[PDB]
Length: 283
Ligand SMILES: CC(=O)SCCNC(=O)CCNC(=O)[C@H](O)C(C)(C)COP(=O)(O)OP(=O)(O)OC[C@H]1O[C@@H](n2cnc3c(N)ncnc32)[C@H](O)[C@@H]1OP(=O)(O)O
Ligand SMILES: CC(C)(COP(=O)(O)OP(=O)(O)OC[C@H]1O[C@@H](n2cnc3c(N)ncnc32)[C@H](O)[C@@H]1OP(=O)(O)O)[C@@H](O)C(=O)NCCC(=O)NCCS
Image (tube, rainbow, N blue to C red; front, side, top):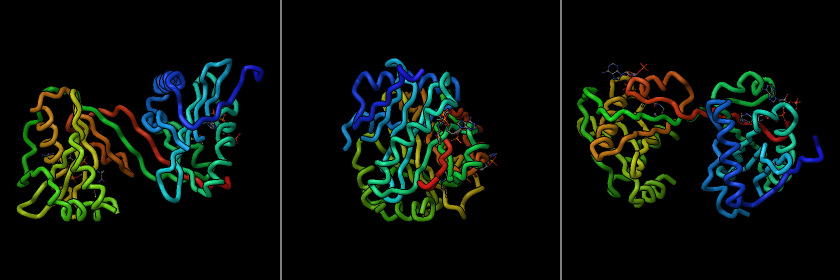
């Protein structure tokens, strides 16, 4: 019923809009299993008008936002209340966002999509699958037994920049500045895995009060398949539990779901899974 429809276009979300968006997020999560990446901490800050809110009678039923991370693409999050899907809401929101993307002269759009939900018809429309991002959690208080490999583990320091940059150069090709900034945030640590005296991998740890989060996990391609990734992740799990945390979270990017079996074996369960699909503007 169009009388009650309205689209609000904003530079940031006030506290009520954030509450509304979190309610919408929750109802999509229950229907879909996973949700797009919304970067709530970015929406809360004033930016210089990339959030588009669809209300029906003042109830938030649709949301789209644009995120200028890349220098030659833009990330797009779109969510529509399950009650109101297939009525053109997502298409209305994308149309509102396009002028702003064109004006910035970006031409490539990258959408984060709940795992498995849309693959059939994203393919039809010409989207290209890029990779997936999985957020997992291990809520077991028991440490991981075994998984011992001939590795030593070191906490990285500002002196390990060559080692860290070398690892990233092979896995995931200004890394000096990024590792310096990470190593200067007291919530972060990086564990380096050594085989004899050659660095062969690393994992980042972000510490919070009740949990810690593993990310940016790398094992050199030529050293994979020897148990080293499992040994490093087990080392990290046990380090986190020995500080008294009750949860280990994990953020991993993969092009293939089978790479996830390692983490399932170590007791992780998926809490959120997104697939990233790109498309050029003129479509
Ligand atoms: C292009 C994107 O928006 S990727 C968004 C990924 N986000 C999510 O998946 C979050 C959970 N899912 C949702 O919120 C919704 O299902 C969305 C955002 C994917 C689509 O929202 P809707 O308002 O229902 O989409 P809308 O009704 O505007 O349809 C837009 C187009 O996509 C098509 N479409 C939408 N959903 C589907 C679907 N499940 N299956 C097949 N086609 C679909 C429509 O046929 C339409 O095509 P058309 O322009 O040729 O007529
Ligand atoms: C960490 C990662 C790279 C794998 O590293 P790895 O050293 O090859 O991992 P492992 O050798 O420990 O494990 C490989 C397999 O052997 C199993 N394994 C490890 N130790 C084992 C042990 N004692 N007993 C039985 N199985 C074991 C693992 O469960 C794993 O499962 P799979 O065969 O079903 O796939 C991968 O899991 C990943 O996360 N990829 C996405 C992130 C990424 O690609 N970063 C860039 C790397 S270049």
